[PDB]
């Protein structure tokens, strides 16, 4: 897939960041190359349409690298984007979950029964995405799927999200 | 302007957040309404094309709510987006700049831009101008040329515009 290649070739890997032995996958070059960013959004949108058809009501973007992809992905799908933030940031009534960071969402972000796909840049342990799913569940939203550009498969984040489906463009050990 | 109205109607105000006496302007509903979001990006893009023609090399988006607009704006203009992040998040060699929020620090990769490259900075809202000023400083230290800073909202009583001068500033909407 030449589109996927446009994305993969713009992932930059930094050894020993932030700790010795870890390899950080830097997605910033994807954003800097407009053809790469377009390919990433296109591939995610095509997957989501092919999997869910018209069932998705909103994209939920995770603070803050999910914010980079969520709105463009939503726009490509003709959908709005709701925001899940680090705690203390959102005004008005909210719910929060601590996973030690805390996520937050406005109580009126979604109505009961609305269906959402959650997007972040990368899935590692799955802690962040798992917390997002729980928050959304407490609004009585249905999480159809979580998606990311990158998945670190040796950390088994996918298993953590089960039974909510997960999809990534690229996988690294 | 029907387009501008689509954006203004989707700004929500929260008095006494985060402190008593102020009014937080919430842009979240703009993102939730795809017509509103499209209008905001379109208005910003049209302004930038009308003001700079083809001279913009990159959009620089500010962590974290600038990230919501930066890539879509960049895409609309056919440009890439570079990131200015809260300190501690970026790999590789970086520069950072403090400003009062106590203090916060923004950071950029030393290799984000080459000397002479021309950039427009975007954030959701301009208040005191501290955040945008820090971004401008970082970019200047890379020897990039900051053509303009833009936002959806400007709180004019806080005089952030003057703080950025002589770098031009543009907002879609203004409140006291
Ligand atoms: N871009 C990038 N983000 C990472 C990396 N490791 C962790 N993250 C960030 O941390 C979260 C995923 O970590 P998790 O909660 O799944 O362990 C995501 O929000 C992601 O932005 C990495 O190697 N690259
Ligand atoms: N959406 C929103 N952001 C604000 C508000 N006040 C401060 N900010 C955030 O803080 C920064 C602007 O504050 P400044 O540094 O100009 O005083 C921006 O990054 C913006 O995201 C507000 O009322 N609404």
Image (cartoon, coloured by chain):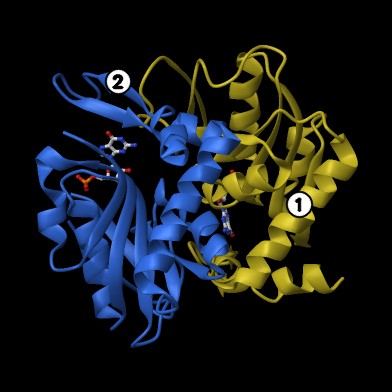
Chain colours: A blue, B yellow
Seen from this angle, which residue lies furthest front? A1
Mark 2, residue position? A14
Task: Say which of marks 2 and 1 sits in front.
Answer: 2
Residue A14 picture location, percent across and down: 30, 20
Q: Which residue is painted at 22% across and 61% down in the image? A: A131
Q: Is residue A55 left or right of residue B163?
A: left
Q: Is residue A35 in sight in this rendering?
A: yes
Q: Secondary structure at mark 1?
A: helix
Is the residue A77 above or below the residue B118 in the image?
below
Badge 2 crowding class, 10 Å Cα cut-off, few under 14, some 14 to 19, many 20 or more, is: some
Residue B83, placed above or below residue A125: above
> In this orientation, which residue lies closer to the viewer: B161 or B150?
B150
Say left or right for A69 vs B152: left
Q: Which residue is mark 1?
A: B44
Q: Picture coordinates of residue A168 (x, y %)? A: 30, 49
Q: Is residue B139 left or right of residue A62?
A: right
Using the rendered image of the protein, determine whether residue B100 is visible from the camera's viewpoint.
no
Rendered location of residue A64, percent (x, y) = 41, 48
Relative vertical location of residue B157 with respect to residue B21 in this rendering, above or below: above
Give the residue drawn at x 47%, y 40%.
A3
| Marks 2 and 1, how far apart at CA | 35 Å
Q: Where does the C terminus of chain A fall, quadrant-wise?
A: top left
Q: Chain of mark 1?
A: B
Q: Residues within 10 Å of mark 1 (few under 14, many from 20)?
A: many
Q: Secondary structure at mark 2?
A: strand
């Amino acid at each position: 897939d030449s589109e996927l290649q446009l994305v993969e070739q713009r992932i930059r890997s930094f050894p020993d960041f932030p700790t010795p032995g870890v390899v950080f996958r830097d997605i910033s070059p994807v954003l800097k190359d407009p053809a790469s960013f377009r390919a990433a959004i296109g591939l995610l949108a095509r997957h989501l349409k092919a999997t869910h058809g018209g069932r998705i009501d909103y994209i939920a973007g995770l603070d803050s690298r999910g914010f980079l992809f969520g709105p463009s992905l939503a726009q490509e799908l003709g959908l709005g984007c709701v925001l899940i933030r680090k705690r203390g940031k959102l005004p008005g009534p909210t719910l929060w979950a601590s996973y030690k960071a805390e996520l937050e969402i406005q109580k009126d972000a979604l109505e009961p029964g609305q269906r959402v796909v959650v997007v972040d840049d990368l899935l590692a342990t799955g802690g962040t995405m798992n917390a997002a799913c729980e928050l959304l569940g407490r609004l009585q939203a249905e999480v159809l799927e979580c998606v990311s550009l990158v998945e670190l498969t040796s950390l088994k984040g996918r298993e953590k999200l089960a039974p909510v489906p997960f999809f990534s463009l690229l996988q690294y050990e």
